Image (cartoon, rainbow over all chains, first blue to last red; front, top):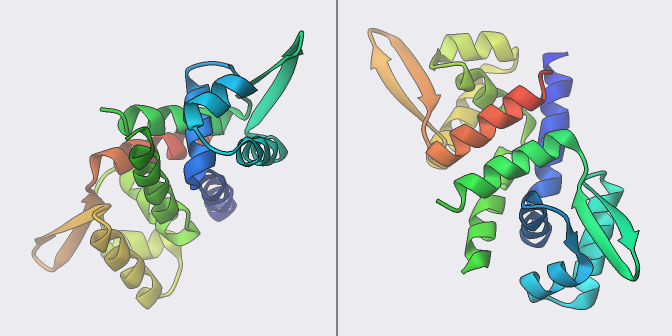
Length: 93
Length: 93
């Protein structure tokens, strides 16, 4: 129904409407980032970032892959990634 | 700071992450709507819609103007309107 769509969308927004997680998502809008890249650009507790990434992964918003001993996170869900790009662009001008 | 921006953005998302208000915002993405247009397309209590509009107005997300005895609401905040367009597009395909 017209409404289940609005519920899905508002649930996505709910998942994005968190300062730390949103910042991660914006860093990822500019391309895949390593856990170190993230932690350094966020300047927030190692455990905080780990849990924020874990949550975003759980919610299907980001994915990760390995190379050597560096893990690279990237945006995953198509709808979320587009929304996050718009949010990133609009809150930077 | 890099962070006050993420706080502003997450506050916008917070304001949008509500089924009824989000639906109003999506109806407005396609252009200004009268209170009757809204109430009919939402199929929800007269008072509910009134309060949702009032809230969105309070938060600077919509504006209204009069013509005769019809009030027309339209999207107001530029950042929110762009975000809502992206949300509308992405949750309709």
